[PDB]
Amino acid sequence: ESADLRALAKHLYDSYIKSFPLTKAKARAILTGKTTDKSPFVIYDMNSLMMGKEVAIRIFQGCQFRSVEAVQEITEYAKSIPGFVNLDLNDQVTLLKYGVHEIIYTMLASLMNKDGVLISEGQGFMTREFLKSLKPFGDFMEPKFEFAVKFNALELDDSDLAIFIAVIILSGDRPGLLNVKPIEDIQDNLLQALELQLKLNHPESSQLFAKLLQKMTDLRQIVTEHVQLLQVIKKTETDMSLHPLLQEIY
Amino acid sequence: ESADLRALAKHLYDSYIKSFPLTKAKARAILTGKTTDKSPFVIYDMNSLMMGEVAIRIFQGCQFRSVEAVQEITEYAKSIPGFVNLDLNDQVTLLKYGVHEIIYTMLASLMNKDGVLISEGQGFMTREFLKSLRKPFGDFMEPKFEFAVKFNALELDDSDLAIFIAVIILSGDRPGLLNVKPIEDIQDNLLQALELQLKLNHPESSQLFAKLLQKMTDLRQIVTEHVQLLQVIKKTETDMSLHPLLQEIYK
Ligand SMILES: CC(C)(Oc1ccc(-c2cccc3ccccc23)cc1)C(=O)O
Ligand SMILES: CC(C)(Oc1ccc(-c2cccc3ccccc23)cc1)C(=O)O
């Protein structure tokens, strides 16, 4: 009934707030928008960054660090989705493994506008053109920027995004899953809760449910495109015995 | 009004029939060995291939059929209300990015786990036979079978597919589009039409609408993979001619 759907929605919203550092609502206030309580430090050039083992590699590695960190926040959020911990533990691991990249790029949009991205929990702001100003690394944020511009045109808020992220985790078509049935049964429930949420939250945005789902197609293409860049960078340099243990962590 | 959505659904179903020679309904009647009205001849090896008469031959068959399919899809496209009224450059762009996604959607209608109908249903070519084709060509069809088997478990019929196919063409998040808003206004209507159609045609089937739209992710991947395998073929087969139309669509 509408009752357990709204219950599910509020549950997810509550744990999404608890699990992640900067909400979209706060990121929007910082960006383009209102509140400049404390302006973020802006990174627009090589100087700016320093004023903030090596620049272009420094920045791409920094994004990896945050993303490893984010995997744990996503994990904790996953385990708050009703039914998730009851799944086969191999399937939990699989769902997280193939889901975290799509989740990261989804949420990255919350931190982006067409001009740049908030980092360090909104304390910083790296400009889009400074990012594109790199060498075989000026290639890696631009498709995220192009995706975010289109995705943010849907004007979702955190309550919408909480359910959407849960939908992504409970996919069903991840390779190697052992028991697809309960996963799809949970996702069917989450899709219902999502549909309702979007109808109550955006009553005059017609077919917002459908439009948001079609965005999954662009999301997977981003992820695919990102892993192939990663494979190229794994041909920039791999041999060095000065962070073997840090290499491990990533 | 739901009434307007029903008329649009009827209209699109109607054009689909008139545009596409072999419907899913006919494909299923052929495939199910309980209607012996006219059974297909089955191609499962090279001698049955020669009885029912290599890899290049088969794939250029596929190439010619695809170009004709583009024609039929193009014909169907003009019947979608609002489509011919769009900026022409966008009409080209919509077709360019839509055509292959639709071909693999419809291809599934002619497939089961064991093979695919060919030559307007007169032939059936085995999945194993296609998989054993020489090294580059043996990998072309297998991901389409994979898609088709899970897509076919949605159990869509032609009146469903007519609207879904229209939804695909009228995307708008396609690259290079000049006027996105009028494209999205039309898709928005196709989507309402699709949503109603599935809930009436499949009352017991929970969130079929969402699960169908998720399938759009899979069609993208198929196209992407097929493209990268075509550029392999282009280099190992310098003597094989890719069709100019198909060439213009791929970039
Ligand atoms: C889950 C998410 C979106 O994870 C992020 C991952 C990477 C970045 C990021 C993106 C681009 C450059 C960066 C440089 C240093 C640190 C982080 C980045 C921002 C957020 C977040 O922090 O909300
Ligand atoms: C739109 C569609 C799906 O177009 C087709 C495209 C390719 C094939 C096909 C697929 C695989 C092998 C073939 C060999 C000879 C001729 C055609 C094929 C069948 C149909 C159709 O005819 O319904």
Image (tube, coloured by chain):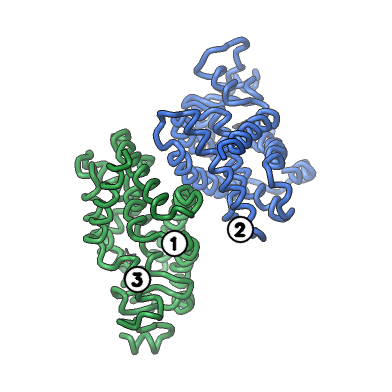
Chain colours: A blue, B green
Which residue lies most toward the left here? B85
Q: Mark 1 lies on which chain?
A: B
Q: In this view, does B222 lie to the left or right of A82?
A: left
Q: Where is residue B18 in the image (x, y as percent from the top left)?
A: 21, 61
Report the residue at 37% width, 69% height from top.
B110
Given residues A149 and B103, the one toward you in this image is B103
Report the residue at 60% width, 13% height from top.
A39
Give yes or no for contact between labels 3 and 2 (Cβ–Cβ under 8 Å): no
Q: Which chain carries label 2?
A: A
Residue carrying label 2: A175
Q: In which quarter of the image is residue A163?
A: top right
Query: Is residue A54 visible in the rendered structure shown here?
Result: no
Q: Quadrant of residue B76?
A: bottom left
Q: Mark 3 lies on which chain?
A: B
Q: Name the quarter where the C terminus of chain A is drawn.
A: top right
**Marks 3 and 2: same chain?**
no
Report the residue at 43% width, 55% height from top.
B202
Question: As shown in the figure, which amino acid type bears the numbered disc 2?
Answer: Pro
Mark 3 and mark 1: Cα distance apart in space? 13 Å
The answer to whether the residue bearing label 3 lies less than 8 angstroms from the nearest atom of ligand 2 is yes
Residue carrying label 3: B27
Ligand 1: which quarter?
top right
Mark 3 and mark 2: Cα distance apart in space? 30 Å
Mark 2 and mark 1: Cα distance apart in space? 23 Å
Question: As shown in the figure, which amino acid type bears the numbered disc 3?
Answer: Ala
